Length: 371
Ligand SMILES: Cc1cc2nc3c(=O)[nH]c(=O)nc-3n(C[C@H](O)[C@H](O)[C@H](O)COP(=O)(O)OP(=O)(O)OC[C@H]3O[C@@H](n4cnc5c(N)ncnc54)[C@H](O)[C@@H]3O)c2cc1C
Image (tube, rainbow, N blue to C red; front, side, top):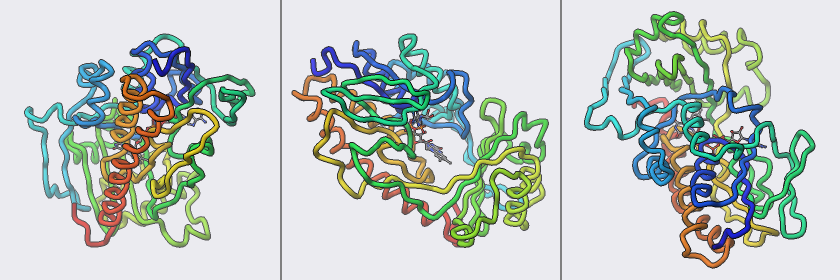
């Protein structure tokens, strides 16, 4: 009854926003999702996601999508490999644990979520630019100069959201590490040396402060990421131009001088690199207790943190579960109280996850680290 005759708008059709949409809409709420991506066919760059039983999988179950997730997810082994290609540990998958946290492609996840929504729930090509309250409703203005209205706004548009003002003025901060990601499509053909070294398992390696993570089978592509402490020179002078492949390759081949040729080949064979400083949206300061209209935040928009904890999507999916529950479970007598309780709970597990992620980051990039 809280949401009677209420138009709810979710900003962002990432995993968290689509899951929030589903959890509300299945209860007959009036939901719209605004997504900047041009259309549903847009390729989502990055690695695979794994849903944990007590958070992400619980959200999928509550949404009716757990078996669909299992159908499309792949259980993956993991090898810890030294810089010379020697496997130090092979942690293959046990049929016992195949459903513990199988890896799902990000586009596959978006599709099962989209398929669970009514048609035309997501409005594509809508990059929200301004969000200001008018009367008792929010005014949403998009890059394409269109405008829309809503009674409640849930911000789920990622860690770099520019529309957080009415919730908090806290700013994103860099943590001191940097990540470079890329894909090699059809790796069996195009990087056979490294693909064979992976041996059908995810690969992790750490050397001289440089971490390499790779997944040889993300829907026909090998995805890899190289992470390190941000060079201090970058702080003032830019040394690597991430629009110039050859600039990136020259830097990485320098860093990877001591590594086996199969790793150097992987770098030489990548057509395009994506470089990003690790960031956090810290939960140190409380959010604003006075807001002009109902608004809150979920996912990375709420608690962006370094991904080396394996945290990330599962916290966001718990946000959607708790916020959706609060809004539909009859326990609260206003939207504001339902939101405030959600934020209370999220700050709790969010602060915990952020603290673990910073510890792990400090440990993983120390020169003594060994997995
Ligand atoms: C290098 C790296 C590796 C990671 N690895 C993992 C991992 O292994 N496991 C894990 O669980 N997590 C991982 N994470 C984190 C995980 O990807 C995020 O937690 C997760 O994607 C957050 O989902 P979200 O829906 O909050 O935001 P996002 O996935 O960022 O989705 C936000 C959506 O909003 C859209 N959007 C943005 N701005 C606007 C706008 N103005 N208007 C409209 N729409 C907009 C975006 O296009 C996008 O669709 C990793 C993160 C990084 C950076």
